[PDB]
Length: 118
Ligand SMILES: [Cl-]
Image (cartoon, rainbow, N blue to C red):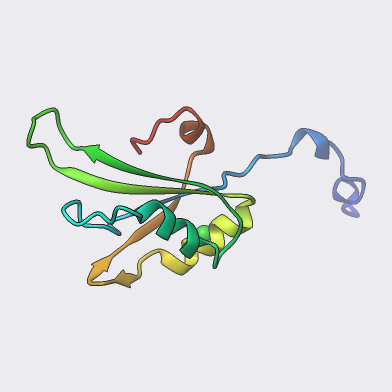
């Protein structure tokens, strides 16, 4: 036709999506060498990408044993999604002090339910 549906923004109010603003940063930290001020350090560093609402550092057990492996997962919630993705693109697949890190978007609902397992 003439693109009429787009031109009149037909049904646009139904089609809005909420975007996650949460980044998960993986493999950044050895679990045996965790800075006391890690949360603050991450907070300040991430200010190079956007307004940071909060940071949670989570030491995740990989099993139930007393000696189960620990993996450090760093969550950063930014004010807006464009900031989250700026941070992800600056970090993901890159090396820091001999560690190759993974940075990805994390589901907002899971984060807001304190489900830090993914
Ligand atoms: Cl991205």
